[PDB]
Image (spheres, rainbow, N blue to C red):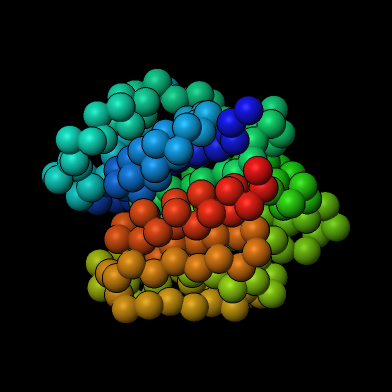
Length: 221
């Protein structure tokens, strides 16, 4: 019976009065469609449940293929510790919202710990790796320690101008937590697999990140 994928997205919108965010739509929609095409059972969750806010910079070029993804985001499940089991993979799309509601969320930390402990696939794109910054194995070892990873880069963050409003810088912090960070050109498709941990750099990496998940799941048929 089919592999099962848990997708978890942000519900955060606030940075300053002049700067709002949310989920970066493509980072959910393109993976969701890939997983649905493969026949996987996908559970769509968010930190809060309900209707997920989209980063306004991410809603202007919606693909006609994204209709079902978009609709799924209007009525998400609220992430639970129960979601720590029953799934072959977890996938964390980005958007700057994640920097504010993923890193310190105890439910998500608990879920990622169990996925890691259990040898399942953990994938994240762009700011999605924020969910990993304070996630650990049971023994306290950071999940990213000694692992090859990518994320939205500090250079990309400085270019967009929002580095000064981030609680921490994601690439910097992942390296500080013990990750071996790697990247490609700003705004190019770059993703990496290190065993069970798969990461992508930016919106342009959404598809390749998802395809790495598919390949890892295909191995475990």
